[PDB]
Structure formats: structure tokens, C-alpha cells
Figure 1 (tube, rainbow, N blue to C red):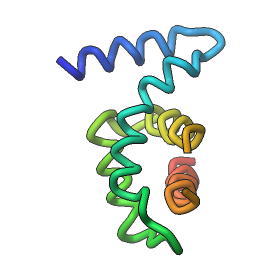
Figure 2 (cartoon, rainbow, N blue to C red; figure 1 turned 180 degrees about the horizontal axis):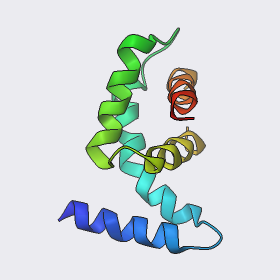
Figure 3 (cartoon, rainbow, N blue to C red; figure 1 turned 180 degrees about the vertical axis):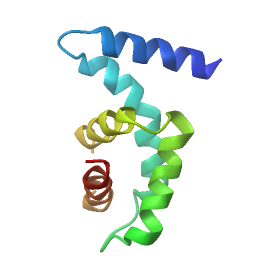
Length: 96
């Protein structure tokens, strides 16, 4: 399944030393696409109470809550809009 393939990616990412960002970029690709589809045309100010739940809902489509979210979020940023960037940074502050 798609879940099994994605787990092979995570296996290779976490085993890797130093951490392999090319593998993480593959992991982040569909997540970035989904986030850009929700927020790519958003300009102006973020709305935390609305946008953060939506952002977390997207993350949950791909990966279970935890340290995977932090890696994905950081890697998504590498491939991008100040709106989505700001949203990501607010979630990262929460995940700290």
C-alpha cells in the first residue's frame, strides 16, 4: 500500500547517518503539495485558530503525530509564500 511504501522511506531516513535530506524531500513532497493546495494562494495574516487545525489535519493524512511532523514541516519549508511559512513556524513552536 501507499502506507507501506512511505514506511520504507522513513526506515531509510532514520537509519541514515548523517540524516539524508534527499529521502526526507521525497517524504515531504506530497505533504508540501497538499499544503500548497490549501494555503498557496493565501496572502496577508495567518489565522491560528482556523489554520493550525487545518495544517495538522493535512499532516495527519500522511504521518502519525510525533517527531515525523517536525521533520516534515522543516523540509516543506525548504521547498517554499510567507503565509504557509508563518503557519509552519507557529506549529513548530507548539511542537517544541
